[PDB]
Image: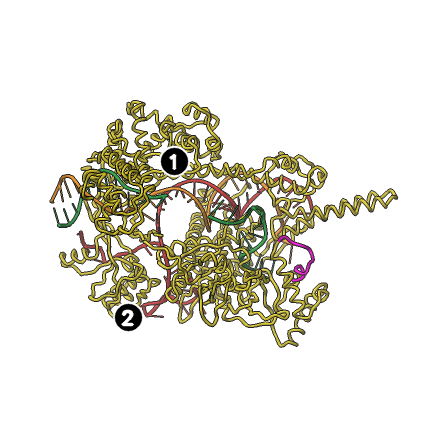
Chain colours: A yellow, B red, C orange, D green
RNA sequence: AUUUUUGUGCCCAUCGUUGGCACUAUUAAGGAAUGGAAUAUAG
DNA sequence: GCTATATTCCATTCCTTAATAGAACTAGAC
DNA sequence: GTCTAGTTCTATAAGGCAAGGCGCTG
């Protein structure tokens, strides 16, 4: 029920004397250079593992003694690594030779794993182990003795101990406790418990431990049996009894005996090493004298990839075995028939090169409907010619042959509308062998080919060394500390300096590479965020209390916007533009402390100092653990719906509600509390712009720029295109340009759209790429209305960045060609560095735009939950669980559109953020039917689904809308469950407006519009509702949307609400019962 | 231990009135997608 | 009606999963 | 009295498929 997370603060290193920063850098260089030594050594230790080393263990979970050995003996690593490479063919032979037996299925699957042949190769770690023995002159029996002890101590194997512990037991020369003493003592405790198994009091239990230890006190007991180290749980019982905090605690004799029996194995030996002195000597030669902190720090970096990749690879092998078990090899013959397409005459290749077949190549399970249509044509064609005795009807069948093509051609094109277009030739070939293979078998065969290729291509994880980071702290690490604010105050008072500053100091014990001795030194850091939320001190007496959350942030209740003195204001106006932003923040900081507005921050040695040295740059990070206690007594449920182009929404439901609006949900009283859209507003001149929806200024205020763009297009407005045998069409892009140049259009849409048109222009003028160069810089870079200068967090702004990157791609590709060595970033940078920089600037800008959107959306969701929690109580935030949206069976455009969703990225941020607050919990839920369920009716107790609707005026009606509505009236059946809702909803539209299909069907759009206008005018309404997939509105039984208007739909009264607001309620209601007893 | 000029970023035809905001860091691989140039296909 | 399938070669993005960011202690050194 | 620099510590159920959850713009 205890949760732990870390909050990190990045900082800037504020340098000191070159010589002072040189000493720190030299130390950092020392740990980094040494780290690869431990990695090579531990890999070698892994090679020494054998059956006599892992005989009778827990072997983690669902693992095989063989797999544990194979992962240690053989690893996939870079080709240029020191360990000798081995061919995958010899893996089984080497395993048998070392093992003395053949490898099992798990070991075999491991060897079978895919990897990049060009970048990595298998390495024989066993051979590396021999190198250690030969190089260090070690007895095989002696190293084996040490290896066995290391395994018991968790220095090697599946579950590893901390680097600090491993270094201490392996290389420590400090006084160690006597294991024999603990072993007799633990056995005696077990013995008395067996002798008196019915005790049910801690008091009886504490007496037994003391009897076992032959002592009257825990202190005396600890001195004899566990002289040094943390207190064991058994002794902890005696201790807590003396302080009387465990008197009423439940006693379980079997468990105490069982836990004690498990810990017995570790005390059968005294840890007397035989090769540690030699090994320490080799290490000393390569990394210098043994120190616990330095050796431990290097080992931690070395051990992480070795231990982590072993865990990941074992899970991977087990998953792969299961995936292979899932494949139906019994369907392999059917796959052969389907795969026979390449050898048929329906597929033609110059080099006869085939490719993998997937379900989307036949339209997945739709081929079943198509087969039926084909059979009806065939059965009708048989009867026709059976009762068409007259000969010379070759055309009858020839006509039937043509009908088959059109049936397939229609099928492919129809499936192609909402998905990838299936292959006509493949389908024609399959119909030829219709007698040969059943249709269901075809799907099964095509699925087997696709599934087997996917599982077979999965790659193993290579073992790659880490780029090291070193940690300084109060305990179990390199000694380090952040000077405390009180210490800071004292320091400045003793130096006769101003009481407060904006710099942070740390004192860390560092090694002098020259003297090879430890020294403590001070280093200065700078991090306004750390100062504001932690470090700056509340000097005033009677300062506000520390917040429930430690950090002093706006979300935590500290507004931090105090009245500024005129002297402070001058400093901001006075400061250079580069420093104005930081100074204003500091001035407010000094203002809130001066005005006693700064809340206190409780200080503890809770901050870790992480230092990373890249070149001469030092990256110091301060991170602290944040503890939280789970609270499962939720009173409010906050649902979150995530959208790509529309606004995200949230809805809160009160639980165990009693009041005017209470609804009884399956015996649970709930009250919809509120719903809303997630928007991030930024103020400008008493004007606020939502960062998630702003699409840019209208063109009329951008007339020079739009006209400036027009002048360039005019020079290259001559573009040729060929469609439907339309070669040398002499297409004009400027016509298309004006369509987007309307003053009513948003700038971002214009800029994104202009990029595409420019993209097409370059395609026509392939040898005139160079000319667009300067226009691109003004469009994306230098221009005042350039993409880099103005952009929002809206979906359209992101697409604009997408098109801009593609456009640069086109300019580079066209810039180089035949009139073959391949173009690389090196060539493009050489050919055009400025443009190359522009691509990087756009990439870096988009990544910073994406990080922000995730953080700002996360804060709004967390802020609402915190607001609801204070008024009502513990809140459970629920978000849709979105996964596997990008698939190869979907159109690339659909996949490209889906990539910008960011739902998982936002949820991970919310999930991480929720961990810092008590009374807040986050879980993901199934999003199935969340857009079509009538909230608070559906599942109370009946199933209630309704279609999404669009609203517009008769002039706004489009042919697409007209077609959509009719399709819904089709009697053709569908696998999509939601299809029923649209047909049912489409029925209401005819019923509600007194129409008949004949009026909608076979009617010009214009005439259809007139019909709809005459009805609306009679009813005194200007807008009409129609069911549209992805519709903006939902007819809800309840008034979930505050701006909803009641309407009578087909004899029923519903509230027209934003569909997204409805969805947020639906998300909250998914498995709502499980959340409450 | 004193640097006094900066933690990282986000928004805007008006870049400031004290403009308005937000935020866990790192390592490494893997999975699934995308862009551009082109080739082969069937229209 | 932006033709679609597939492939090659150069680049990208969004996300997941293995890790790091130790706790409690005391003999002996200030 | 504190603090450092080393040691040892741990604590031990629920559907199958696959659609659903997303947007366009002329």
Identify which residue, A48 or A871, lies in the foreground. Answer: A871
| Residue that mark 1 sits on | A58
Quadrant of the frame with the C terminus of chain A:
bottom left
| Secondary structure predominantly adopted by residues drawn in magenta | loop
Give the residue displayed 50% in from the left and 48% down from the top: A809
Identify which residue, A867 or A118, lies in the foreground. Answer: A867
Near mark 1 (Cα within 10 A), the count class, few <14, some 14-19 or many ≥20, is few
Position of A160 with respect to A538 (left or right) is right
Question: A664 above or below A520?
Answer: below
Please tell me whether mark 1 sits on a helix, a strand or a loop. loop
Expressed as whole percent of the image width and height from the top left, the position of residue C22 reads: 28, 46
Question: A747 above or below A123?
Answer: below
Instruction: Count every numbered label the image shows and give the total.
Output: 2
Q: Which residues are magenta?
A: A965-975
Expressed as whole percent of the image width and height from the top left, the position of residue A478 reads: 24, 43
Tell me the subunit letter for badge 1: A
Marks 1 & 2 on one chain:
yes
Judge whether residue A814 can be spotted in this image. Answer: no
Is residue A968 located in the magenta-colored stretch of the structure?
yes
Expressed as whole percent of the image width and height from the top left, the position of residue A978 reads: 60, 57
Judge whether residue A714 can be spotted in this image. Answer: yes
| Residue that mark 2 sits on | A563
């Amino acid at each position: 029920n205890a949760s732990e997370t870390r909050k990190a603060y990045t900082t800037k290193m504020i340098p000191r004397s070159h010589d002072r920063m040189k000493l720190l850098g030299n130390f950092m260089d020392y740990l980094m250079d040494g780290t690869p030594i431990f990695f090579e050594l531990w890999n070698q230790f892994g090679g020494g593992i054998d059956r006599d080393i892992i005989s009778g263990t827990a072997n983690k979970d669902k693992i095989s003694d063989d797999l544990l050995l194979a992962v240690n003996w053989f690893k996939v690593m870079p080709i240029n690594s020191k360990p000798q490479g081995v061919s995958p063919s010899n893996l089984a032979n080497l395993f048998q030779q070392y093992s003395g037996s053949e490898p099992d299925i798990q070991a075999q699957e491991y060897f079978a794993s895919n990897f990049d042949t060009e970048k990595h190769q298998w390495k024989d770690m066993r051979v590396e182990y021999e190198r250690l023995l030969a190089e260090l002159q070690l007895s095989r029996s002696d190293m084996h003795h040490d290896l066995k002890l290391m395994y018991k101590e968790k220095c090697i194997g599946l579950s590893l101990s901390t680097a600090h512990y491993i270094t201490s037991v392996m290389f420590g020369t400090g006084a160690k406790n006597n294991r024999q003493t603990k072993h007799q003592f633990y056995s005696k405790v077990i013995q008395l418990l067996e002798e008196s198994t019915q005790i049910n009091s801690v008091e009886q239990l504490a007496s037994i431990i003391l009897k076992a230890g032959d002592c009257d006190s825990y202190r005396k007991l600890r001195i004899r049996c566990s002289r040094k180290g943390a207190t064991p749980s058994i002794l902890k019982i005696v201790q807590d009894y003396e302080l009387g905090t465990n008197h009423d605690d439940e006693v379980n004799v079997p468990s105490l005996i069982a836990n004690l029996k498990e810990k017995l194995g570790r005390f059968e030996y005294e840890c007397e090493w035989k090769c540690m002195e030699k090994i320490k000597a080799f290490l000393a030669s390569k990394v210098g004298p043994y120190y616990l902190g330095s050796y431990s720090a290097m080992l931690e970096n070395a051990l992480s990839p070795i231990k982590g990749m072993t865990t990941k690879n074992c899970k991977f092998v087990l998953k792969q075995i299961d995936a292979k078990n899932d494949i139906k090899y019994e369907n392999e013959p059917f796959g052969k028939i389907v795969e026979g397409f390449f050898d048929s005459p329906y597929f033609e290749s110059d080099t006869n090169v085939k490719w993998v077949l997937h379900p989307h190549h036949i339209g997945e399970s739709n081929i079943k409907t198509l087969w039926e249509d084909l059979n009806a044509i065939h059965s009708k064609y048989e009867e026709d010619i059976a009762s068409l005795s007259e000969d010379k009807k070759e055309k009858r069948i020839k006509v039937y042959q043509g009908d088959v093509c059109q049936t397939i051609n229609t099928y492919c094109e129809e499936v192609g509308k909402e998905a990838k277009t299936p292959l006509v030739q493949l389908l024609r070939y399959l119909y030829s062998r219709k007698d040969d293979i059943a249709v269901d078998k075809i799907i099964d065969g095509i699925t087997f080919l696709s599934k087997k290729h996917k599982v077979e291509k999965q790659k193993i994880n290579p073992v790659i060394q880490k780029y090291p980071s070193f940690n300084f702290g109060n305990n179990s690490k390199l000694l380090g500390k952040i000077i405390s604010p009180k210490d800071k105050l004292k320091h400045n008072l003793k130096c006769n300096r101003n009481q407060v500053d904006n710099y942070i100091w740390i004192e860390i014990k560092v090694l002098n590479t020259k003297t090879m001795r430890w020294e403590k030194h001070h280093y200065a850091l700078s991090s306004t965020r750390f100062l504001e939320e932690v470090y700056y001190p509340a000097t005033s007496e009677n300062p506000p209390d520390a917040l429930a959350a430690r950090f002093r942030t706006k979300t935590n209740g500290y507004e931090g916007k105090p009245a500024l003195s005129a002297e402070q204001i001058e400093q901001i106006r006075s400061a250079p533009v580069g420093l104005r932003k930081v100074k204003k923040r500091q001035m407010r900081l000094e203002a809130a402390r001066q005005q006693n507005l700064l809340p206190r921050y409780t200080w503890g040695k809770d901050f870790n100092i992480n230092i990373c040295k890249r070149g001469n740059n030092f990256e110091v990070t301060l991170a602290t653990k944040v503890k939280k206690k789970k609270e499962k007594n939720y009173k409010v449920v906050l649902g979150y719906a995530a959208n790509i182009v529309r606004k995200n929404t949230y809805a809160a439901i009160e639980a165990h509600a009693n009041g005017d609006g209470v609804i009884d949900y399956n015996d649970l009283p709930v009250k919809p509390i509120e719903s809303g859209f997630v928007t991030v507003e930024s103020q400008v001149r008493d004007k606020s712009y939502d960062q998630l929806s702003y699409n840019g200024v209208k063109l009329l205020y951008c007339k020079p720029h739009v006209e400036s763009r027009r002048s360039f297009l005019e020079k290259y407005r001559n573009g040729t295109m060929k469609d439907n045998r339309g070669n040398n069409i002499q297409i004009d892009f400027m016509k298309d340009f004006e369509a987007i140049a309307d003053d009513e259009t948003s700038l971002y849409y214009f800029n994104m759209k202009y990029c595409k048109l420019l993209q097409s222009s370059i395609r026509n003028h392939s040898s005139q790429a160079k000319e667009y160069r300067e226009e691109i810089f003004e469009l994306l870079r230098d221009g005042k209305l350039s993409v880099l200068k103005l952009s929002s967090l809206s979906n359209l702004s992101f697409v604009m960045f997408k098109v801009a990157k593609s456009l640069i791609g086109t300019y580079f590709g066209h810039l180089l060609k035949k009139p073959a060595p391949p173009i690389t970033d090196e060539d493009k940078q050489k050919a055009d560095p400025e443009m190359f920089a522009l691509r990087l600037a756009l990439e870096e800008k988009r990544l910073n735009k994406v990080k922000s959107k995730k953080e700002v959306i996360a804060n709004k969701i967390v802020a609402k939950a915190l607001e609801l929690r204070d008024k009502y109580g513990p809140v459970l935030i629920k978000g849709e669980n979105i996964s596997d949206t990008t698939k190869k069976g979907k159109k690339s455009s659909t996949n490209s559109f889906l990539m910008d969703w960011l739902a998982r990225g936002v949820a991970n941020k919310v999930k991480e953020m929720v961990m810092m607050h008590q009374g807040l919990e986050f879980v993901e839920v199934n999003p199935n039917f969340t857009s079509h369920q009538d909230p608070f009716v559906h599942k109370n107790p009946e199933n209630t689904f309704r279609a999404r609707y669009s609203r517009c005026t008769p002039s706004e009606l489009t042919e697409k809308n007209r077609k959509e509505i009719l399709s819904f009236l089709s009697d053709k059946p569908s696998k999509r469950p939601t299809n029923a809702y649209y047909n049912e909803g489409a029925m209401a539209f005819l019923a509600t407006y007194g129409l008949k299909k004949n009026d909608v069907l076979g009617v010009s759009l214009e005439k259809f519009k007139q019909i709809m206008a005459n009805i609306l005018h009679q009813r005194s309404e200007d807008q009409l509702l129609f069911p549209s997939r992805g519709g903006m509105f939902y007819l809800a039984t309840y008034k979930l949307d505050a701006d909803a208007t009641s309407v009578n739909w087909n004899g029923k009264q519903f509230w027209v609400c934003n569909a997204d607001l409805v969805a947020a309620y639906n998300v909250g209601l998914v498995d709502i019962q499980k959340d409450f007893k």
